[PDB]
């Protein structure tokens, strides 16, 4: 029912579209795609992906301003300035802002002007914007919000199981470090950048960069304000990343008790979001994983009874997209006028 | 003696500056760089390089626009429009245009309008009025008064030409094809994203990527005799630097054997091409050619003639360093032959 | 209908088992594996694969030596000396020798002595008395009673042969050279360490590595007419799988054009080589050929004739999957026609 | 003055030999090299390295059982069983055991039998063996010890700055995670291994493996027994690794105070071992670094006043070798018999 528009047909743009195609009876409906690239570009890359692999569906370049996916036709436009996009003309109810530039009130807004009704930012919001992490506080949402951010790929992982911890052992304080696959943001070869680290090789180094997911947790778990904070390491992998949380709780606890708690929630409340895995695996073994976070049980370890460390895997691309969809999936429900 | 500017402080441009620094006593003298990032972004990257490794020398940030390599200052400006450049004010004699954008007469010449005397493009010209030179081959063909805009060809073409010559000039090249397993480059996407060439748009780091290349045809530009006889493709493979060419031209001459073809190189190597060509008999691998001053190196043990007429060669060349080194020789030339004597895409 | 054993549970052997599982109804029936690691090490790696991705099916560990793929059991033994193998006891009809060690008559035959009926080597034979087949080319040449030890050639040779044929058989191949940008392989060092070939001893992951290859010559083994006319090298590049060949043979025929050379393939592709050859006109890259059932795929837009006589082709082939798929066809055949040094780099 | 024998001319074997060639007036003197590989193998790989780059020196294959380095001649033998090596015949005073197999009393001992006097194990010792980390307790050494281990590449990094912490803020407890380059130990392609993780792709994954450096710290810093423990992540890089320590100290402290302390020690006592770096760099920027550990100051962060996180780089190959040499450099001094 709910008409959707994908702006920024990049990795999350496409990982999303596809994430969608796989859902059954989706309140969402993609109708237009806006990306600096021509219909050719949109077709090819939606069909041939170097990380998700060739898309199982018939994808042809039907039209001069459209592409076809199993028959469902979609228009492809291209204006580097949103205001122009015919969101109003096409009655765009929701826009999936995955460009990486329009992350602020001012920017995301240009979509509203174009005639769009709502703008889901596929990234953390800059400034005063509603941030929601499906599984951590989606009930906070109200059809009243015109601009929401579905947080970062990291936060969307770290959050779910942080809630589980605090909500059970009480997080006093704690740092975290996310060994992360690289992203479009990094330079393929030592080239200029505003982050002289991110500006480096990307594929030949462990690139320490900073992440907001640290304080962003607090954004959705008000309780942890200023209790968490960490950095990130960009290692030579195109996808799937791991977080290394280290919190100090009040209630003395032990290894398996922690994991247990996780499982319990993963089987009840967080079913579909969090999950545990005992089988000793590795990065690649976590591609296309519909869940936001996956605890590597056998790794979890406690110290001095109150210092807990938890490792957790997550597909920064797919898993996130599945969340983005789940959020938009929500906007479609609890939508009045 | 001669004042030099470097427009484009990236890989090739920085590889340049490096090449130039630790040198005999080049008549060249870099006094300005145009890196759209300031002294910070321009310094850092000159000091710490992922492919060349930390630069060996005190590099400090003086002024708010004037870093220094061991005391010697280098003023640094930044503007996408050459016209606004202080070439005249500073009195720039040579400009190393290493951006890959200004490669046509009109463009690269914008530097002259700014007050530049001569412009060297670190890539093939898109025009036709611009001379393409390849040290080792036809460098003599360059003399003052003859065009104030030249192109040091391609990294590939500058690796091919040299040994392509010795082949035809001492065996007669009928015609042939060629391929080049090439280290990925900045023009490629890091991860699958929009790009005018749906091949370069694929993860440069996880694919063997086929992409056209003129480097083959352009050989003629320096070796007319071959005009329209060579040709080929290129394959991008997950290797940040150092590449190899796979030439397959069926010769005109008799039907010589393998190891003699080599000897020709070996001969022309320690002779006329002493500094350009070379033959390495010891079985190594790409990484062993990092920082190689030779514009081309043949893998002895790889050469092999098939049907008496068909010869096959394989050469090694560092695309960053090597080329940059020639680019400093070609700019070294300009100075030795200078008076005092006689739909815009990609990203 | 026919009991099969798999000696060597690594890449090619595992790629085999997988290929075989999700199949129409192969007469083959894997009942035993010989992975020097037990049910654990042999299971895990069948379920989770870095290049094929988590195997889609319930794989559980029954017994202490008998895992099961969706209920169907598979007994697993382990011993470096085939002679000690229970081939006879179990009554093994075919053995997929995928270790890369037993590739000579004396060796691979040790399986017969243990009680094996027929042995298929997943690599080129080092002997001369062993037949080299390449589905699509000369598979007919195989008939029961004719040697109980065959070789499914090389990954490269099985990619070349097919389209090499169509070239000579419909244009006449004078002779030519070839190169193959090849995904690194197990025989290479991870980091610079001792290895009988100072090229393979270099970091497989950070070098373009030149290494000899007979795959070129061996074409003859299936296509006699070419005997001693082809040849070439190989280049290892940091890419875990999927490779490309660069053939440059100056033809005998007229001086045909590019796009027609192609048409021959295209013709012979949907015709006699329907399942082996194929031509992809859409500009893709290596990663797009993962899990490709075709023994060879030509990049249309890459083909190009130079001097009327010199033709140049480029083909795409998944070295793991593709080959393994043929190896299941060649084992599928057997059944349809049924009544210094020693070590050296491990 | 001290005759040395390199057994296991692998990465640490060669990284060492070369590390040595660069030292001025070295009490050490290499005379024999034992590795499964022929004189060819020893030459080539000592000259052409894919990580240290071609060796600046003339390296030829002089002899049927020797190689030459700038004239200095060295014998190359090859027996998979130590006992045979002519250590006694050549009067081998010290053996640099870098094979990865002879790490126990029984094993390393076969060297003693061959006629060798001492055995320096280029790895952690298994069982009851003297473990010393140059800069952390080399004074514990005594010419009495016939078999010593120079700990692991990780421990040799983590130790130095742990001492600094505890010795100043008092480490109560703390975990750590080391994002580590891969090593000869990993499988290049999913192949059998006793560690089904290490058995995976290596270059395509973040491979969680376990490390002893956790408890090994205590080995050399008796005080921290059972206070530290962590895991490790093998990421796609051939060299240089980073450690992510997270200790809880008693004495409340803040960001820059910690770093300060580090610098102080790095300028005085640990001068040559530890060191700080403010210039925002990345992996590759730390090749050939003579020091054991290097603190990434700008990354150091504190929480709730007592939870300290410190990131630290280190060249698991070179820097370690330089330590190995420094240890052997010591055995030569304070050597009586
Ligand atoms: N990569 C990941 O793992 C994750 C990313 N995200 C977030 O999702 C967003 C997208 O990230 P990612 O997909 O990785 O990035 P990409 O660069 O892959 O995708 C962004 C796309 O938007 C296009 N684009 C840029 N500007 C415009 C414009 N003005 N109008 C139309 N199209 C435009 C870009 O084209 P061009 O580059 O040519 O301008 C590109 O195709 C970011 O907010 C990111 O933080 C969230 C979770 C995970
Ligand atoms: N790398 C190699 O081995 C070879 C490359 N070449 C060619 O040389 C050229 C440069 O290659 P490479 O060194 O890899 O590229 P880089 O990306 O390293 O360098 C290009 C530089 O130009 C800057 N720049 C971009 N646009 C402008 C502009 N409009 N005005 C001023 N400066 C600008 C870029 O900054 P920013 O990115 O921020 O826009 C960057 O600093 C290309 O044509 C390439 O094909 C030739 C032979 C070999
Ligand atoms: N990978 C590919 O794309 C292609 C490979 N091939 C060829 O097929 C062969 C196998 O290749 P690949 O699958 O990559 O190799 P793998 O390493 O995956 O498989 C070889 C297997 O044999 C086992 N093994 C080793 N020695 C013995 C022994 N003495 N007795 C019993 N089992 C043993 C190995 O165990 P362990 O390692 O523990 O000793 C391993 O499980 C090689 O000849 C290769 O050249 C042919 C075409 C393509
Ligand atoms: N890699 C690193 O970063 C670090 C490693 N170390 C330690 O140093 C040791 C060596 O590690 P590393 O250098 O990485 O390993 P390598 O595998 O690179 O080196 C060991 C070498 O010894 C050879 N070898 C094995 N057995 C014999 C034998 N019986 N006789 C002669 N030669 C033999 C091996 O050949 P082959 O494999 O064919 O048997 C190999 O060439 C291990 O203890 C390791 O834990 C310490 C710090 C860091």
Image (cartoon, coloured by chain):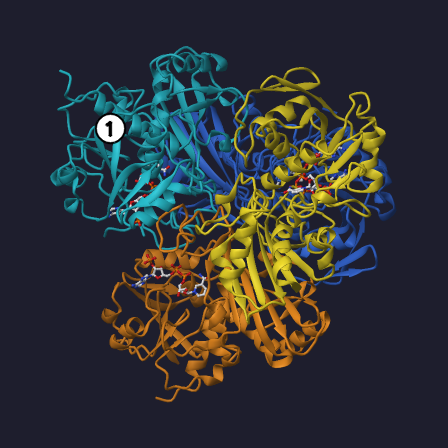
Chain colours: A orange, B cyan, C blue, D yellow
Identify whether D275 is placed above or below C146.
below
Image coordinates of residue C270 in percent, x first then y, are 48, 46
Q: Which residue is mark 1?
A: B132
Q: Residues within 10 Å of mark 1 (few under 14, many from 20)?
A: many
Of B246 and A286, the residue lying toward us: A286
Ligand 1 lies in quarter: bottom left
Which residue is rendered at x = 31% and y = 34% of the image? B214
Direction bottom: furthest residue: A336
Of A33 and D121, the residue lying toward us: D121
Image coordinates of residue B192 in percent, x first then y, are 42, 54
Image coordinates of residue D225 in percent, x first then y, are 74, 59
Identify whether B23 is placed above or below D63.
below
Which residue is rendered at x = 52% and y = 45% of the image? C274
The quadrant in which residue D125 appears is top right
Image coordinates of residue A175 in percent, x first then y, are 55, 67
Identify whether B300 is placed above or below A249.
above
Residue C152 visible in the snapshot: no
User: Is D280 on the left-hand or right-hand side of B227?
Assistant: right
Identify whether A5 is placed above or below A49.
below
Q: Chain of mark 1?
A: B
The quadrant in which residue B25 appears is top left
Does the beta carbon of the residue at mark 1 sit less than 8 Å from ligand 2?
no
Q: Quadrant of the C terminus of chain A?
A: bottom left
Residue D274 visible in the snapshot: yes
User: Is D88 on the left-hand or right-hand side of B183?
Assistant: right
User: Is D52 on the left-hand or right-hand side of C300?
Assistant: right
Q: Quadrant of the N terminus of chain A?
A: bottom left
């Amino acid at each position: 029912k709910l008409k959707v528009a994908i702006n920024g047909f990049g990795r999350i743009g496409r990982n999303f579209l596809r994430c969608w195609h796989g859902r059954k009876d989706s309140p969402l409906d993609v109708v237009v795609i806006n990306d600096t690239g021509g219909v050719k570009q949109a077709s090819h890359l939606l069909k041939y992906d170097s990380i998700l692999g060739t898309f199982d569906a018939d994808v042809k370049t039907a039209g001069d301003s459209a592409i076809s996916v199993d028959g469902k036709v979609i228009k492809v436009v291209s204006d580097r300035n949103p205001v122009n996009l015919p969101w109003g003309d096409m009655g765009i109810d929701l826009v999936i802002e995955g460009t990486g530039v329009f992350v602020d009130r001012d920017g995301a807004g240009k979509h509203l002007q174009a005639g769009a009704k709502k703008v889901l930012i596929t990234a953390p919001g800059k400034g005063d914007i509603p941030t929601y992490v499906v599984g951590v506080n989606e009930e906070g949402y109200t059809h009243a919000d015109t601009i929401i951010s579905n947080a970062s790929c990291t936060t969307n992982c770290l959050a779910p199981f942080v809630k589980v911890l605090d909500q059970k052992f009480g997080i006093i304080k704690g740092t975290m470090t996310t060994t992360h696959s690289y992203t479009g943001d990094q330079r393929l070869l030592d080239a200029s950048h505003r982050d002289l680290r991110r500006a480096r090789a990307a594929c030949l180094n462990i690139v320490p960069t900073s992440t907001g997911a640290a304080k962003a947790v607090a954004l959705v778990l008000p309780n942890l304000k200023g209790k968490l904070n960490g950095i990130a390491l960009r290692v030579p992998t195109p996808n799937v990343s791991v977080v290394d949380l280290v919190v100090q709780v009040s209630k003395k606890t032990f290894a398996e008790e922690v994991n247990a708690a996780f499982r319990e929630s993963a089987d009840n409340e967080l079913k579909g979001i969090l999950s545990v895995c005992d089988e000793p695996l590795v990065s690649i073994d976590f591609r296309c994983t519909d869940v936001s976070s996956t605890i590597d049980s056998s790794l979890t370890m406690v110290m001095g009874d109150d210092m807990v460390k938890v490792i957790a895997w997550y597909d920064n691309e797919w898993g996130y997209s599945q969340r983005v969809v789940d959020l938009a999936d929500i906007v479609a429900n609890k939508w009045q006028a | 003696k001669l004042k030099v500017a470097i427009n484009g402080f990236g890989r090739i441009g920085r590889n340049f500056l490096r090449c130039w620094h630790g040198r005999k006593d080049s008549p060249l003298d870099v006094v300005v760089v145009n890196d759209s990032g300031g002294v910070k972004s321009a310094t850092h990257l000159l000091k710490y390089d992922s492919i060349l490794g930390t630069f060996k020398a005190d590099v400090k940030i003086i002024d708010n626009e004037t870093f220094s390599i061991d005391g010697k200052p280098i003023k640094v400006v930044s503007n996408r429009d050459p016209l606004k450049l202080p070439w005249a004010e500073l009195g720039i004699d040579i400009v190393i245009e290493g951006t890959g954008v200004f490669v046509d007469g009109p463009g690269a010449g914008k530097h002259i309008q700014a007050g530049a005397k001569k412009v060297i493009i670190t890539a093939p010209a898109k025009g036709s009025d611009i001379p393409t030179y390849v040290v080792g081959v036809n460098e003599k063909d360059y003399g003052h008064d003859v065009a104030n805009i030249i192109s040091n060809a391609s990294c590939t073409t500058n690796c091919l030409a040299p040994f392509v010559k010795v082949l035809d000039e001492e065996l007669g090249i009928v015609k042939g094809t060629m391929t080049t397993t090439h280290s990925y480059t900045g023009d490629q996407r890091l991860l699958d994203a929009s790009h005018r060439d749906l091949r370069r748009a694929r993860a440069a780091a996880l694919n063997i990527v086929p992409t056209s290349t003129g480097a083959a045809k352009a050989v003629s530009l320096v070796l007319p005799q071959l005009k329209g006889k060579l040709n080929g493709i290129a394959l991008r493979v997950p290797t940040p630097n150092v590449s190899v060419v796979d030439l397959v031209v069926n010769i005109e001459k008799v039907g010589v054997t393998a190891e003699d073809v080599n000897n020709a190189f070996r001969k022309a190597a320690a002779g006329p091409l002493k500094g350009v060509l070379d033959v390495c008999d010891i079985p190594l691998v790409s990484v062993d050619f990092r920082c190689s001053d030779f514009s081309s190196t043949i893998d002895s043990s790889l050469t092999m003639v098939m049907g008496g007429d068909m010869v096959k060669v394989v050469a090694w060349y560092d695309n960053e360093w090597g080329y940059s080194q020639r680019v400093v020789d070609l700019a070294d030339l300009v100075a030795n032959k200078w008076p005092g004597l006689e739909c815009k895409l990609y990203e």
